[PDB]
Image (tube, rainbow, N blue to C red; front, side, top):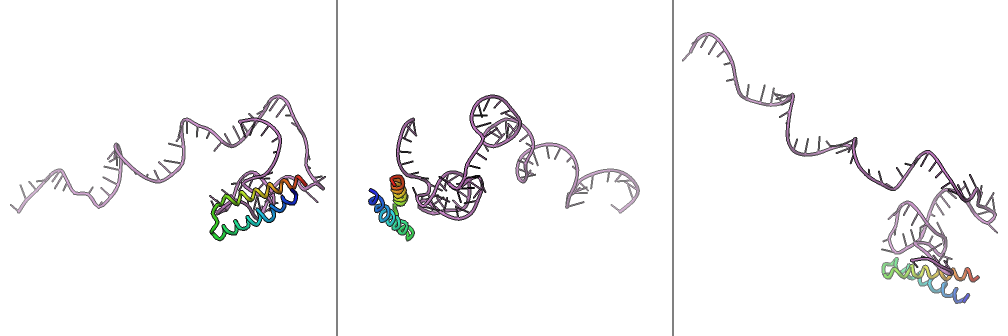
Length: 53
RNA sequence: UAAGUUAUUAAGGGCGCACGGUGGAUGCCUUGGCACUAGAAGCCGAUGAAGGACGUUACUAACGACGAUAUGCUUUGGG
């Protein structure tokens, strides 16, 4: 859905990535494979929203 | 302790030979080039061009690829 697609990307996958990058810099964030996995999730959400228009 | 005569020494050097260094010629190689044949095909840009700067990865100087959807995203067919 138009709104659900936006809500999931804005509050989730964005603030979630903020914590990962923040946690890593402090030196207490393992599981590095979770950043790239979330980075590309936003790319797919913005691909559907742009073509659906 | 007479008259006469002729040798060794090699501080160093010369010639020959043996065995080592320095140096990168020669032989054998090719990821790179040069001269051509035939068939395409001979422009891009204000709907922002040709070339550039700065950025993008789990840590990333710099080469290639990408542009805040950043070392990639979707879909349609090959494997």
